[PDB]
Length: 306
Length: 306
Ligand SMILES: C[C@H](NC(=O)c1ccccc1C(F)(F)F)c1nnc(SCCOc2ccc(F)cc2)n1Cc1ccc(F)cc1
Ligand SMILES: C[C@H](NC(=O)c1ccccc1C(F)(F)F)c1nnc(SCCOc2ccc(F)cc2)n1Cc1ccc(F)cc1
Image 1 (cartoon, rainbow over the protein chains, first blue to last red):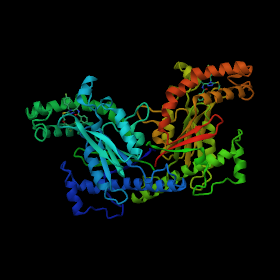
Image 2: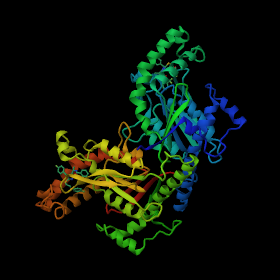
Image 3: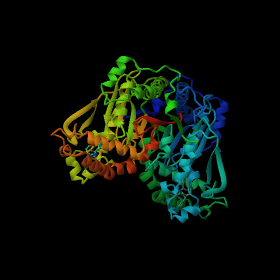
Image 4: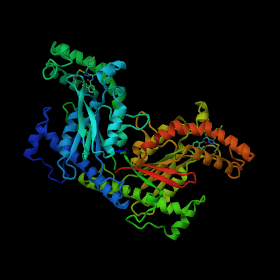
């Protein structure tokens, strides 16, 4: 006996969920438009039921806000609407956190209950390269201490406060650095998705996940993520690495075989250990774990018992 | 702005609040049953409203479980009813956690949504004195490592799993040790309250506060808790210390003056440092912070915005 309800591919797919849960052609066009060669069959058979389950929790939290406001005879110091409902998205580099997150942002905005949905990545809260250097942490980008934890906690707290205005900094992956002067403004959305390696990480004191209303961990066999990491790396030889401004131009194209080999070594030396030491242990902390098989198709969902 | 809604005493009192909330006389009689000279005016004027607020969260969770079971077309692997709703209660030694906990236990069982409310203290998860010897930890009794944290995690996990049967050990304060062979059995309650110094403490992997649905922190100025710790040590001269089976039986023989000196020492040397290091840093992780005046009456509630 476990604290999770477990579903295989078959039962999950088996949309007994008696909304004829099917997207329209307008929407499917829109969803192509996040093109990580996105498989619209998974969006409709898997991510749509998931947006639905999460929808039930957001709507529940919204009536609990109403009932509670009514009970407290709605006094001045109580807010006028619910604060943003915050979803955390965690997993290894290259498992597809960002794609999952973008898809949920899109699906969840479909309901009139919560149409304004924001997405922030914790990437924006890494220390600038210059600062990482000052601390001797360059070889540790994406490990817990390479993030300005205070700023990230201030950011999320302010969002949970129901501020009209919360600012995050912006990270360019192209430049391998924080963009000086850039800011993403978040203005009391109904939902805010927060995606990052570290979102479910444990801290001595108050931590970001203490402000999450729901959380998701994207999982896969460690070997399978290695393969996805390697492939994205070779593929980047065009798209990004090719660009002159790319911090990683000194790789831009140096033999497929030698790119495989370097990718494997960056994986084994940085990203894989960050996974074992720091990310995987946060897995049992998620409300929902999604396990994908070799070709990114979901084969197992574990959902915390309500 | 902050993540908290704040009430002072008068505001909380003002139960012109959308429902009449008064206790009946059979209720007030029952509530005297634990009447360590319980202030029954506070019980009806502060704790009743507090239990109502919590009830709203319990009932929300019950509906969400049903809306969710129906969306999932109710599978064999989803449980038939909600699993226990778990409330944590934390704060210093002598701050009145146990009283607080016992007053919400009886009050919450008032509603037919959730009549079966249990109470467990984490004291039952301290290592027995003998195992605490092997480890050189007798001087750290009540510090995070004096607990069998693995068994405490297993116990709370098993309850959140909806199992019919979960056993906690039993601590005797009289004998200053775990009673060998004795067990408290928990059998799928609607609500389980978990009271302890350590309930909201952080750790690297999964931690018990992950499995909570609501949590309370009982608060006061450190001066005042010292005053209550001291008063209770003196008072115990007559009561528990007087028992000849009392592990602290030699404390019965203490003059007032000697008792003040000794109590003041145990405090400023063991309990006060535990408060400052391990217990007080957990205060912002609570859903609700109850602050008490020197006289034991509540004077601030801080509640997390919904
Ligand atoms: C460790 C570093 N981490 C990140 O850049 C990073 C840091 C924080 C969040 C995400 C990421 C990212 F997804 F991009 F991997 C990394 N992990 N992979 C690389 S290569 C440049 C980015 O390339 C890829 C390749 C595949 C991929 F799936 C995502 C990004 N780096 C930069 C780097 C290369 C060599 C070296 F010796 C030190 C660093
Ligand atoms: C630090 C210790 N803590 C625990 O026993 C303990 C451990 C876990 C939870 C609760 C408690 C308790 F509240 F009872 F204090 C303690 N704190 N107070 C004492 S004296 C016996 C219990 O007396 C009181 C006195 C006041 C009070 F509010 C609660 C308990 N001890 C045992 C002890 C005495 C002398 C010495 F040198 C070392 C230890």
